[PDB]
Length: 278
Image 1 (cartoon, rainbow, N blue to C red):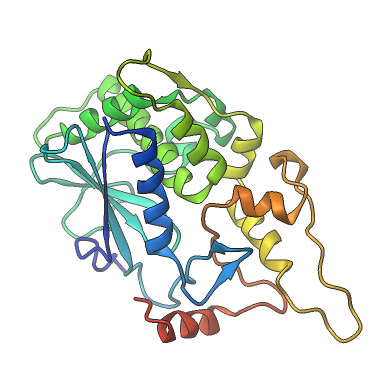
Image 2 (tube, one colour; image 1 turned 120 degrees about the vertical axis):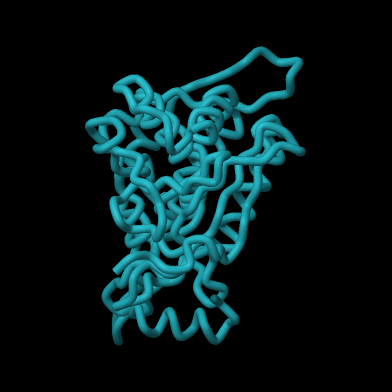
C-alpha cells in the first residue's frame, strides 16, 4: 500500500526562485498543461484525470526549486492525480515524507501535509506571508535538511512554515489562477523593493473548496435530460465566484469529480488513455 513511481516522475517542472514574475507564470502554466487530461476540459480549463481506483498512488511529478540557474534544487514529490505534496528531497539526497510509510525509503519529517497539520486550522491561510524571499527561505530550510540533524521545536516550526509556503506558491497556485496571479503580482525585478502580501478570504475559501468549485463547474457541462434547459452555475459566494465565467477564470486546473450525468472515473480514465495520457 506504499506509493509507486515516486522517483519516476511523469514530468519535472523547474523554477529558479530569482526568476521573473513572467517566468513564474510560465512555470505554473506548464504544470497545469502537463497534468491535464487532454480528453477533458471544462470551459477551456484543464481537468485532471481521475484518481486510479484500487491501486496506491502511482502517478507523480516533480517540482525542482533552485536558488540560481546553476544550483542543485529542492525536489518536491507531488501526486499527478490530485496535486498533493507528499515528499521532498534535501541536498544530501534524503527523501522526506509527509505521511508516515507512504514513500518507499523516505524519512518522515515529523508532521503531516494538511493545513490543519501545518497551521492548526485551515482558517489560518490568510496569515501566511507570500513573496519572493518567503519562497527562497522555504527552499533553503527544506533543502538544507539532513538525516542526522537533531530536531527541535524551532526547526520543526520552520519546516512547517516552509512547507506551507511552498504549498501556497506551488500547489495552490497550480490549482487556482487567483492564487497564481496573486503570487505572480508579488514577484518583481531586483530594482524593486522586496515585496510580500497575504491572500484574502475569497482565495482562502477557494483553496479550502477546490473539489467543491471543480464539481460546481463540471455540473454545467452535463447535457440536460429530455426537456431541460442546461444546468446553470451555482454561485459559491464565499469564494466570490458567482458565474461559470468567474469559475473558469478562478480555476487553474480542475480536480476530477464524478458528478451526476457526467463522466465516471472509469470512463474519464479511458478517454485519458485514448488521448495518449499516462
